[PDB]
Length: 341
Ligand code: NI
Image (cartoon, rainbow, N blue to C red; front, top):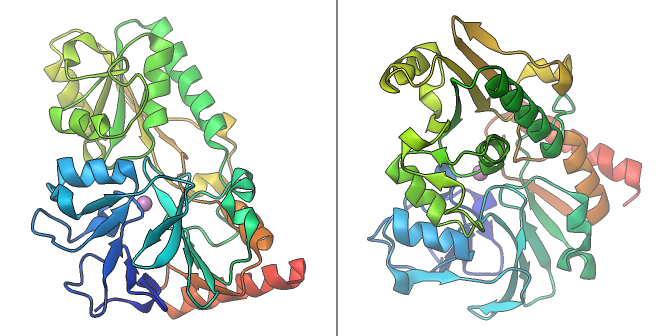
């Protein structure tokens, strides 16, 4: 049955609640972004109204075959009326098409649901700055102080410099990047741009990327692997066996692989700077795990909450154990006492 933290009080709404069947009393289903733990349950047989961003709506129509008459895309940063309730969609700084949702309840309560997000000071100047928020439904994925990671900009600098150096020393090296969902496109797009190549990938992945409104995409991606020296593979194939096999398929065009796995966090972060990251190597294959995150660090999350000053926080991640829940509630209290709200 649907957990309470997916239900919006005083409305007929649910958020990312598609795996529970017909939710009793739900008149509109919101979807924050196209990731499977959030869309699980949607298909061409869905006949309730789904509200989402334009990009998410393109993916629902093209990848899951949801019929168009049930997709309700909304522009960003624009006040809209849904079933008599004012709502706004805000950029979540997560993956393409990902949004936060502001609900203005008929009784005066204002609720922000962050979906999945990476908090940023640029959010302090959106339509959030314009009224008080009473309740915050918060993406708490990395809500513990051990979760530090560098900026996305530093991580991409590392990846570009590493790839450019490797291929300049050996023009017969292939670069491979792993993927399993949308998000983190900058990784493979920035490397292809510094090497003067398109990114080669499967027809199914090319289709997914063509749904995203990324400017000049026909210019950066392709299905012709033969013409490309940056290849995208499923995340599961980024290991020594899967990469040795791939190199066999390239028919002696290449004699070395440099591969990237853009993970969220890994405990190398507590001890090591980005500057100091080294690969795992076997023979002519090297694999780099780089800490490219599309969720808030602990400090980014703290700064956002201390700025917003909500009256009540509802975590949406790590809610399944008492130890996790008690840990998070203790941080929330600290933040409130330190800031004075
Ligand atoms: Ni997500």
